[PDB]
Image (spheres, rainbow, N blue to C red):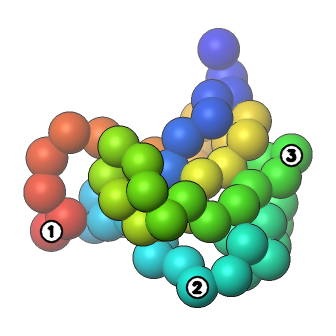
Amino acid sequence: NSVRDAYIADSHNCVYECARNEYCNDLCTKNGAKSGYCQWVGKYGNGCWCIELPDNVPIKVGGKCH
């Protein structure tokens, strides 16, 4: 699998919080995903969720935002 649906993360393992679905669709797609939307509830609470994000871009994994 070179793509996955998940919360996109920065290089510090932190999700990107969101107020708008479009903010997330833009963020996800400019990083190669198919689309994205804002999750206001989810495994890690508020943050952008991307569909088919390539695996050279980070996703939130277990651990802290550091």
Residue at 35% over, 59% down: 45
- Dividing the picture into quadrants, the one containing residue 17 is bottom left
Residue 25: percent from left, percent from top: 79, 66
Residue 19 tag number: 2
Residues at badges 3 and 1 in contact (C-beta under 8 Å)? no
The vertical placement of 19 against 46, above or below, is below
* Residue 20 point in image, percent of width and height: 68, 82
Q: Which kind of residue does numbered mark 2 sit on?
A: Ala
Farthest-out residue, bottom: 19
Q: Are marks 2 and 3 in contact (CB under 8 Å)?
A: no
- Res 63 seen here: yes
Location of residue 64 (image quadrant): bottom left
Is 2 above or below relative to 12? above
Residue drawn at 42 percent across, 67 percent down: 46
Whether residue 28 is visible: no
**Nearer-N-terminus badge (2/3):** 2
Residue 4 as seen in the image, left or right of residue 9:
right
Mark 3 lies on a secondary structure that is loop
Q: Which mark is residue 66?
A: 1
Question: Could you tell me which secondary element the residue under label 1 belongs to?
Answer: loop
User: Which residue carries the number 3 mark?
Assistant: 34
Q: Is residue 48 above or below residue 1?
A: below
For the C terminus, the quadrant is bottom left
